[PDB]
Image (cartoon, rainbow over all chains, first blue to last red; front, side, top):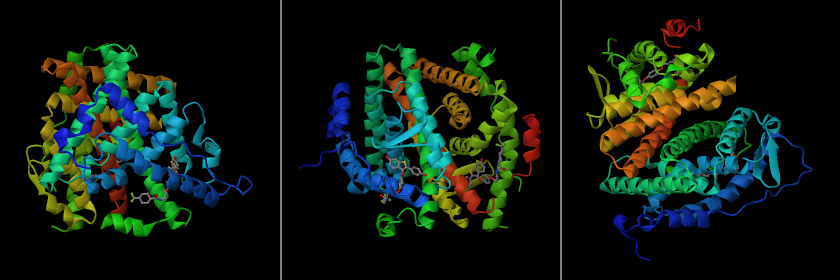
Length: 250
Length: 233
Ligand SMILES: O=C(NCCCCOc1ccc(Oc2c(-c3ccc(O)cc3)sc3cc(O)ccc23)cc1)[C@H]1CC[C@H](C(F)(F)F)CC1
Ligand SMILES: O=C(NCCCCOc1ccc(Oc2c(-c3ccc(O)cc3)sc3cc(O)ccc23)cc1)[C@H]1CC[C@H](C(F)(F)F)CC1
C-alpha cells in the first residue's frame, strides 16, 4: 500500500481507547515450551530450552512490532534497529508480566515454570534470575494491569533504540520526531488508563513515573543478560547465529 | 523522620539546586593511555565532590552507610555521564568534560571502543537541547538516578519504601516546576515521560561504559576518601 508521511501516521489519529485496543490486538500468541521432561536438567539443556522458546517468540515479536501503531511508518532500516536494540528487554518484560502471580518463580511458558534454584544450574544466571524475580514482584506490588503492560512494552520498542539513531541524515531527524510523537501518544494513553481507574492527578503522575523508572531497570537487566548470553555462546550452550549478526552489522 | 518527606516542592528544588557540586577544570602526551589517564584523573576528582553532593540529596542520609555505598556503586557513572551531557548541551558535536577540556566526537577514536560511547553521550546532549532541559529539571533527574539505579538490587523493605517515597516527592517536584512554567496538564505528563525515558538511555550508557572500562584495565586513587566521607571506612 501507500507509505504515509509522518504527519499522516495512523498512530496520531488514534484515541486513547483505540491505542489500547490496537496494542491488545497486536499481543502475540501464548507459546508452550516443546521439551522432553525426562531429559537431565543441565546448563546445556536449560539454555537449550530457553533458546528454543526465545527463537519462537522472536518470530512473533516481529509481527507484533509491525502492528504497534507508529512502527511501520519508520524506514525498514530503523525498524530493524529498534528490534535489535530492544528484543531482550521485550522478552524480559513479557516474562516478568507472566510471572507476576507466581512469587518466587519465572513463568517462561505455561508449562515451564522455573525457580531461582534452577537458575543456579546455569553459571552466571542466578543474579539475572533474582533481578527478574524482583521486577515481577514490583509489578505485582504495583498491581500492573494488562492495558498498562502493553503500553510499557510498546514504549520499550520505540525508546530503546531511538537514541542510537545518530542524527547523521535528515531522515533520522524525521524518524526521531515521529518516535517522540508516538511516545507522547502512548503516555497520553497510560494517563487515560490511570484516570479511568480513578487515580487522582498526583497519583497518575507518580504511577507513570514509577512505571517508567522500572524501564530503566529492565534495560539494565537486558544489558547484563546480553553479557551473560555472550558467555553462554563461548560455551556453546547458546547459538551465536553469527551470520545473522554480521548481516545486521553490515 | 525524614526531612525529605516533610519538604514542599519549592523547598526540594532549593535543596537540590543548593547541593550542586563545583565545576572542575582539568589538571592532568597524547595517546590512548594518556587520554584514559586524563579522563580517569578528572573522574577521580569529580567523585570526591559527587559523594558530598549525594549526602545532600534529601533522603540519602536516612539510609544506612552500606546502602548509601550500594547506591553510589550502582549510579556513579550514570551521574558522571548526566553531568557531562548537561555540560555539553551548548557544544553540539563536542563533549565538555571540563571548561578547559572540550573534546570532539572524533577524539573518542583515540581509545578503542570509546567513540561509540561518545556518540551515545552526544545523542543524549542533543536530546536535552531539543527539549530545552532546565537546570531545575536536571537536578531532579540526577537525584532520581542516584535513588533509582540501585533500589532494585537491594527493614530492607523499609529502606526501599523510603526510597520510593522520596522518588514520589521528586516526581511531584518535577510536575510542580512544569506547572509553574505554564505547561498544560497534557504537556506536563508528556514531558515527565520524555525526561524519565532518557534515564533508560543513561543506564544503557553506564552499562556500556562499565564494560568498556573493564576492557581497558580501568579503583580511583581517592577511593579511601570516598568511603571515609560516606562513613563506610
Ligand atoms: O534470536 C536470536 N538468537 C536465538 C534466540 C535467542 C538466543 O538467546 C537467548 C535469549 C534468551 C534466552 O532465555 C531467556 C531470557 C534470558 C535472559 C537473560 C539471560 O541472561 C538469559 C536468558 S529471558 C527470556 C524470556 C523468554 O520469554 C524466553 C527466553 C528468555 C535464551 C537464549 C538472535 C536475536 C537477536 C538478533 C539480532 F541481533 F539480529 F537482532 C540475532 C538473532
Ligand atoms: O573507582 C571506581 N571504579 C573504577 C574507576 C575507573 C575510572 O573510571 C573512569 C570513569 C570515567 C572515565 O571517563 C569518563 C566518561 C567515560 C564513560 C564511559 C567510558 O567508556 C569512558 C569514559 S564519561 C565521563 C564524565 C566525566 O565528567 C568524567 C569522566 C568521564 C574514566 C574513567 C568506583 C568509583 C565510585 C565508588 C563508589 F561508588 F563507591 F563511590 C565505587 C568504585
